[PDB]
Image (cartoon, rainbow, N blue to C red):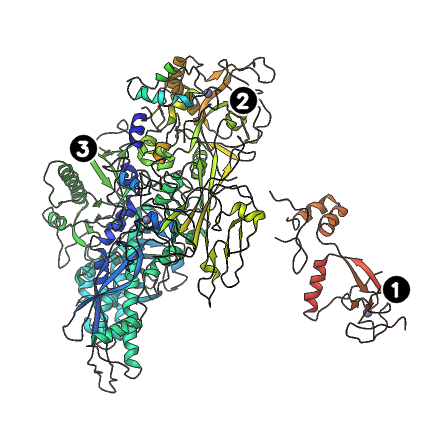
């Protein structure tokens, strides 16, 4: 589901770094290495915000309490 | 009574025991129970 | 390639309103959905019912020497057509806007997804009335997304407007809520005469032999029946067939002269008219003609009448009409149902017996029915239509039988002109069949008066187990051969005989007993299901150099051309191959035209048609051009090399085609086709395998079989899933190493694992015997987080057996109520709180009886703490029903616990052994701890070298930010992918061999040796204890009720020679008991404790009855005085022996065990 704060391998918290990295590919034209601007020196806590699936923005469109 | 959720219409129905079950506003025949406020405690593990 | 992130996000955020984002998936499921459409549309069922015919009924007056037993009031009725409407809302009006029912709701209310079924009944009163009327015969299921559901044509957007996930597939009939599915099964080839050599023939028809020939001929409504040619040792051929589940053997010559008004010279000149005086064919044919002449008759009509008079019984034909028309009925209905022109049937029968004889003398190699060459596929919609037609016909026959018995009683009402009478009889019969189809789809058991030419009759359906998305798709695309061969353990079809290249996946196949039996399709291989007109095919052949003769236009070097079972002409084999080439060329050329701007006329030469040109050779296949246009065939695409265009062919031209694997492999002037890509040989799941062309194949096989059993997301729309057990993993991510088709197929929407920091090292000492370690920190940090959904429903109707109405109602009888548990859990409705933690001995729901007015309860069977995520009040019916069904969806938490299984995507399964402390773990010079430690003792003898490849590739792609592509058969022996990634990584700065210098977590000082560290994709399994000190003992034999010890263990303990241990474990710990015996009489039951001697005094000294007859004497519980039976002792023995004595006394046989 959500980006897993406090990555497994590293001890760095990353949960903050999701929308801040999303709007780097989105409108900054830089490729995935925009995370280098984020400061993930390793590859360990690096490979999370890179290949994380944010499926929950698609699961949330399922409120039966949508009143519509 | 009990308060439920019309599945499609999404309308509180306030149905009572031993009663025909259907949405009152749209007519749907499937309804969930709302989640009341009930104390539950968890460990962070 | 990079992970499509902005695509994925601007995909999720706004679901597409245009169409499905992943067309390859819909194409992947295309078989069943198009089967359903071709059923409803494509005039399929109307063909079935038309070729059903009509049934007659009347008042039969016995002839009594009349010969024409007269009858006037004849009614002949038939159904004109079948009407399948959409599944309206429980049609009968409920004072609401009568809307439709989307299948999501049928899942929710846990009800099958059915739609009304209408017939257009037609009459005849032995005049010409034939007026029509519609008869409802129940409601039958409908498959999801199909041509009669409210979900076809829908874009992911409005699918989200309903409660089905964005990429809904369709393909399953929803019965009772559970996703049922009709499996694809393999049959032989349609209408092509196959050669057969099998011993099982000769032992049954002893005059016969293993040499034989068959054809599974099929009607236009896809209603195949077979008929085998038995070449008997004397020389004649028997025309076997099947009807009423019964075999029937009629001589070929009989049906031949009965088919066409033919002279025996015409037979002889058709069968062997060539090379005048070919020894073998001539003498055998002569013997055949002679042996029929022995008894038979001469003209065609005499044989027709004889046949009708011989077979009028098993035929359910109109009893009264005549006798020769019975023979024509046979000749039209059984012999060769695919064909219609009797003369053409006759020509083909000639060709057939001709080929049969050629096979007799070794002039042709044995066709292999055990090969995908001689084989096609059954769809769902097709068998659905066939069984549907079958029930149609049984319904017609039932109503005819009812009219017949209506006449037969005396004459209760006999007026086949009053529509009232027809209404009465319509009500007289059971007018629901929809439940029959629903029944089968629930069961699969094909209950038919005829096997429909199908070997096995059970297990026809599977359930679309959505445990995991790969399990889902693989369920759709798998095929199976049938347990009729599974009961046969042999080196037979279970082998991968090399005609599947690009047709059905090599590796993708379960292990164990059903290994090899069920194989899934390849990736791209489709099944053509919509035939086309081919009239221009015989026109073009006629203009091309062949011709169908009337008198025998056949000679030695001339081959035969077959249009899906119809002889159309002849030509020498050179002309045959040339015709084949030019025809495919026309097909491909007009294809590239019709596809593009070029006008799309009725295709002269459609793409589906397969040109089975069979070159001639001694002891080979009987050479002959074979054009097939029948649907339900295996058809796969490649590129025709001469042009640059698409090409399709099936498993008949493969064995004769030189299709190059690579644009590099082509050798000119011979290789006429080139594979689109070697990718096109594997199945879906096996293709979704990093560098799958590296590991020893058994590893890849375990990989498919286990990866179909993964704890990933089974979909997105979970909120409305009424399943038994689903599994979802919380923190998912796509791999770093992948084949491109994992992005193409839209697998971004079902991650199944994560990406682990793997370090192969013998450091701990707990990870041997394949075991593995899990970093504590990475585990608490939210590693693979298993979440089970166990969903149970409760229903009150079952406990309403009969005699009373609905009596129980959920909640509490008004008044008293237990608080100690119930009010703490049950809210007020007898229904638990939403999200309240339960335990085993805990009530879940409360209903009370009305009459008794007492509350009952339901406890949690399960034995682990579970919560409740939602409870659902199922509207019991159309409406006007109290809530008699409730659905609780309990969420169970399963973090990675000691004893659960992990596996990379290489079959490298491991087990969570100890969850090492994160600080005692070693670390790189950067320092991040190895999240997972595996052993180096797993890679040798497992050859999982692709694992190392994937590891290096991950280490690189992660650092640079690349979605490492790992499609099989890219990297050559020139440059190893090893070296490519070594460049990637030495660019990253790491070692070229993936190593990295590590310091011991426990000693701190670095290791003498560098250590291998990479980023593998790890998913979690789901396959993952009963103590008993004591408990309940059996009713009969006082055994601990249903741990096993004995009957092989006994050998063990007595092997050690450890008697006391044995008597301890099996007698003492199991059932220990004291019982008396009469020492003299030696019986153990004639013992009894003495009764009522005096006050409490001394002990009641037991005595014997058998050994018996003031202090010595005593009495009975009934008062019978006695004396004697004193010699009594107490002995230890297992009570089960006592039970044996009991039931043996029940036989009057008893042992007299003595004692000392
Ligand atoms: Zn990290
Ligand atoms: Zn409603
Ligand atoms: Zn005795």
| Lower position in the chain sequence, tag 2 or tag 1 | 2
Q: On the image, numbered disc 2 is attached to which residue? A: C761
Q: Nearer the viewer, residue C750 or C851?
A: C851
Query: Viewer-nearest of labels 3 and 1?
Result: 1
**Looking at the image, is C724 positioned above or below residue C6?**
below
Chain containing mark 1: C
Chain containing mark 3: C
Distance from disc 3 to disc 1, alpha carbons, whole Å, reads 115 Å
Disc 3 and disc 1 on one polypeptide chain:
yes
Q: Is residue C709 left or right of residue C1091?
A: left
Q: Quadrant of ligand 3?
A: bottom right
Q: Considering the image in quadrants, where does the N terminus of chain C appear? A: top left
Q: Considering the image in quadrants, where does the C terminus of chain C appear? A: bottom right
**Residue C651 in which image quadrant:** top left
Disc 3 and disc 2 on one polypeptide chain:
yes
The tag on residue C1097 is 1
Q: On the image, numbered disc 3 is attached to which residue? A: C642
Give the percent coordinates (x, y) of residue C523: 32, 38
């Amino acid at each position: 589901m959500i980006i897993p704060i406090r990555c497994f391998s590293c001890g760095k918290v990353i949960g903050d770094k999701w929308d801040t990295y999303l709007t780097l590919l989105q409108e900054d034209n830089t490729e995935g290495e925009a995370l280098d601007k984020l400061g993930l020196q390793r590859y360990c806590c690096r490979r999370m915000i890179l290949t994380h699936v944010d499926l929950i923005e698609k699961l949330l469109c399922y409120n039966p309490l949508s009143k519509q | 009574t009990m308060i439920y959720l019309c599945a499609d219409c999404g309308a509180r129905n306030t149905i009572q025991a031993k009663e025909v079950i259907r949405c009152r506003e749209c007519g749907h025949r499937v309804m969930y129970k709302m989640r009341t406020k009930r104390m539950v405690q968890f460990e962070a593990r | 390639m990079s992970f499509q992130t902005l695509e994925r996000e601007r995909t999720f955020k706004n679901p597409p309103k245009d169409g499905t984002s992943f067309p390859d998936l819909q194409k992947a499921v295309k078989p069943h959905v198009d089967s359903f459409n071709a059923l409803t549309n494509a005039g399929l069922l109307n063909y079935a019912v038309k070729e059903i015919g009509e049934k007659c009924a009347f008042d039969s007056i016995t002839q009594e020497e009349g010969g024409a037993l007269k009858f006037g009031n004849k009614i002949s009725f038939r159904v004109d057509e079948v009407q399948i409407a959409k599944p309206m809302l429980s049609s009968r009006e409920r004072s609401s806007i009568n809307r439709k029912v989307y299948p999501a709701e049928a899942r929710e209310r846990l009800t099958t997804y059915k739609s009304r079924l209408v017939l257009k009944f037609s009459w005849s009163v032995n005049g010409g009335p034939r007026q029509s009327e519609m008869r409802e015969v129940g409601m039958i299921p409908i498959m999801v997304r199909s041509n009669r559901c409210h979900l076809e044509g829908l874009s992911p957007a409005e699918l989200i407007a309903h409660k089905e996930e964005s990429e809904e597939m369709g393909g399953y009939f929803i019965v009772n809520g559970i996703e049922k599915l009709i499996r694809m099964l393999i049959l032989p080839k349609r209408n092509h005469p196959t050669a057969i050599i099998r011993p099982s023939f000769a032992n049954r028809g002893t005059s016969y032999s293993q040499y034989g020939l068959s054809i599974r001929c099929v009607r236009p409504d896809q209603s195949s029946l077979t008929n085998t040619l038995h070449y008997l040792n004397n020389g004649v051929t028997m025309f076997r067939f099947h009807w009423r589940k019964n075999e029937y053997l009629i001589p070929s010559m009989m049906i031949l002269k009965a088919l066409l008004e033919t002279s025996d010279k015409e037979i002889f000149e058709g069968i062997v008219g060539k090379d005048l005086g070919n020894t073998f064919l001539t003498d055998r044919v002569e013997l055949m003609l002679r042996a029929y002449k022995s008894y038979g008759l001469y003209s065609q009509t005499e044989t027709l009448q004889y046949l009708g008079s011989k077979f009028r019984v098993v035929l359910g034909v109109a009893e009264d009409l005549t006798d020769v028309e019975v023979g024509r009925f046979l000749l039209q209905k059984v012999v060769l149902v695919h064909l219609r022109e009797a003369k053409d049937k006759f020509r083909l029968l000639l060709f057939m017996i001709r080929k049969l004889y050629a096979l007799v003398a070794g002039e042709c190699c044995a066709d292999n029915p055990d090969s995908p060459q001689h084989q096609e596929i059954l769809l769902g919609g097709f068998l659905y239509g066939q069984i549907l037609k079958e029930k149609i016909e049984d319904w017609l026959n039932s109503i005819r039988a009812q009219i017949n018995l209506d006449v037969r009683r005396s004459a209760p009402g006999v007026d086949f002109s009053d529509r009232k009478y027809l209404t009465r009889v319509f009500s007289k019969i059971n007018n629901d069949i929809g439940t029959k189809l629903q029944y089968f789809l629930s069961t699969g058991n094909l209950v038919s008066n005829t096997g429909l030419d199908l070997q096995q009759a059970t297990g026809y359906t599977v359930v679309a187990e959505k445990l995991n998305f790969y399990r889902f798709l693989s369920h759709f695309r798998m095929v199976h051969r049938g347990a009729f061969f599974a009961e046969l353990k042999t080196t037979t079809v279970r082998k991968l005989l090399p005609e599947a290249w690009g047709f059905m996946c090599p590796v993708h196949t379960p292990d164990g007993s059903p290994c090899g039996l069920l194989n899934h399709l390849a990736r791209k291989c489709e099944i053509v299901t919509h035939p086309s007109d081919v009239s221009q095919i015989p026109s073009l052949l006629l203009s091309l150099g062949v011709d169908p003769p009337s008198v025998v236009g056949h000679e030695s070097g001339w081959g035969c051309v077959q249009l899906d079972g119809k002889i159309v002409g002849w030509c020498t084999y050179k002309l045959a191959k040339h015709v084949a080439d030019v025809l495919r060329l026309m097909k491909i050329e007009y294809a590239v035209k019709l596809r593009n701007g070029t006008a799309t006329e009725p295709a002269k030469v459609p793409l589906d048609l397969e040109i089975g040109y069979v070159p001639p050779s001694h002891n080979g296949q009987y050479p002959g051009l074979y054009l097939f246009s029948n649907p339900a065939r295996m058809v796969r695409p490649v590129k025709h090399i001469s042009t640059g265009e698409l090409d399709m062919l099936g498993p008949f031209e493969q064995v004769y085609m030189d299709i190059a694997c690579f644009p590099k492999e082509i050798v000119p002037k011979v290789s006429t086709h080139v594979e689109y890509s070697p990718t096109n040989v594997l199945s879906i799941v096996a293709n979704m395998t990093p560098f799958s062309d590296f590991n020893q194949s058994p590893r890849n096989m375990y990989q498919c079989q286990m990866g179909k059993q993964t704890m990933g997301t089974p979909g997105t729309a979970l909120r409305y899933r009424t399943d038994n057990k689903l599994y979802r993993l919380q923190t998912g991510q796509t791999p770093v190493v992948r084949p491109k088709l994992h992005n193409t197929y839209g697998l971004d929407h079902y991650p199944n694992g994560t990406n682990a920091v793997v370090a192969v090292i013998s450091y701990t000492g707990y990870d041997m015997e394949d075991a593995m370690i899990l970093n504590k920190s990475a585990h608490e940090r939210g590693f693979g987080y298993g979440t089970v959904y166990k969903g149970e429903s409760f229903d009150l109707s079952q406990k309403r057996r009969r005699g009373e109405p609905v009596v129980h109602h959920f909640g509490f009888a008004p008044g008293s109520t237990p608080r100690r548990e119930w009010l703490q859990k049950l809210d007020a409705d007898g229904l638990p709180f939403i999200g309240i933690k339960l335990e085993d001995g805990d009530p879940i729901v409360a209903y009370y009886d009305e009459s008794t007015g007492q509350n009952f309860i339901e406890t949690y069977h399960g034995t682990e703490p579970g919560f409740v995520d939602e409870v659902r009040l199922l509207g019991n019916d159309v409406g006007d029903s109290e809530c008699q069904q409730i659905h609780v969806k309990l969420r169970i938490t399963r973090s990675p616990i000691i004893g659960d299984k992990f596996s990379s995507r290489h079959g490298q399964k491991g087990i969570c052994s100890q969850k090492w402390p994160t600080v005692d773990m070693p670390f790189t010079e950067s320092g991040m701890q190895p999240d997972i430690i595996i052993n180096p003792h797993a890679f040798p003898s497992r050859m999982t070298i692709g694992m190392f490849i994937e590891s290096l590739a991950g280490k690189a792609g992660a650092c640079h930010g690349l979605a490492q592509d790992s499609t099989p058969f890219i990297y050559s022996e020139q440059q190893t992918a090893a070296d490519y990634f070594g460049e990637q990584l030495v660019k990253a700065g790491y070692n070229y061999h993936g190593n990295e210098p590590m310091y011991s977590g426990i000693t701190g000082q670095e290791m003498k040796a560098d250590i291998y560290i990479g980023v593998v994709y790890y998913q979690r399994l789901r396959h993952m204890f009963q103590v008993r000190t004591t408990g309940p003992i059996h009713n009969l034999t006082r055994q601990p009720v249903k741990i096993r010890f004995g009957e092989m263990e006994r050998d063990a303990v007595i092997g050690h020679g450890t008697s006391f241990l044995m008597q301890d474990r099996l007698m003492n710990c199991s059932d220990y008991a004291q019982s008396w015996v009469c020492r003299d009489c030696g019986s153990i039951i004639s013992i009894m404790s003495t009764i009522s001697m005096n006050g409490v005094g001394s002990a009641s000294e037991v005595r014997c009855r058998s050994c018996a007859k003031t202090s010595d004497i005593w009495q009975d519980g009934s008062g019978k005085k006695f004396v004697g039976g004193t010699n009594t002792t107490l002995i230890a023995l297992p009570s089960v022996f006592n039970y044996l004595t009991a039931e043996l006394t029940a036989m009057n046989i008893k042992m007299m065990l003595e004692v000392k």
